[PDB]
Length: 252
Image: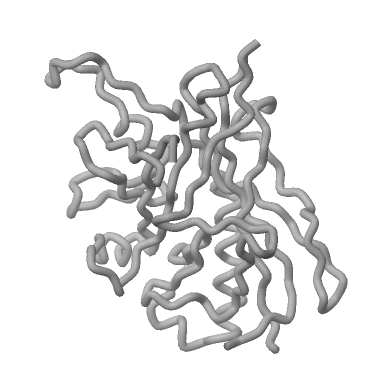
C-alpha cells in the first residue's frame, strides 16, 4: 500500500559546548518516520533537545526526503550513505567547481541489506554519485550536472536503449531537497563558526560551503562551533560507513 521512505533531518540548539566553554551549537542528525505525508511537506518543528545555557529548545529541520520505488516492507532494505568532500583525502574532487559556485561537494551511495551492507552501483557502474545539494552546479571534471534532485534517480536508472539490456530502475523514485531549510541550517553554522573561529573564513568563505551532514570543514577539520551528538546521544553518524535505511513500508 505504501512505499518505504527516508527523511533526513538535523536537530540543532544554541548551547555552551566545549571548544577542544564557548557559545556555539549542539547538533544531531535524525530520521523522520513518515510515509503518509506528501513528499516535500515536512515542517521545521521543535525537537526534544533543550539547552543547558538558556533554556531554549531545539528545532528539527527536514533536509532531504527519498521515497522507495516499489510497494512493500522489503523497501525497508533500501537505504543510503552520504559524506562531504575534503582537501585532505586520497580521492580528489572538483575544487574549481566548488570555488566557482561557492558550494560543497558530497558523495552519496545507495545500499541494500542484508548487511557490511551491499552497494547498489549506478547505471554507469560507479560505486557512488558525486552531488551538490544546490542547483545550477555543472562540473567539468565529471562533465555532469551535480544537483542531487536532477541527477540521482536518473543516474541509478537505465531505460536500456543504447545499453541494450533490460530497463534498469532506481530503488529511490525521487530525491526531494529542502532548500530553504538547508540554507537556514548552513547560515546558522557559518555564523556561529565565523564568530567562534574567525580564521575558518579562509577556506569557508560562504555559508554554501558548510558541510551540514558530517560537519567537516573543507580543510578536513571539524567545525569548532559544533558539538556533534552520536548514537550515545540520540544521534546518527552519517559518512562513508554511516548507514541509513528507508522505513515504514506497508503491504496491505
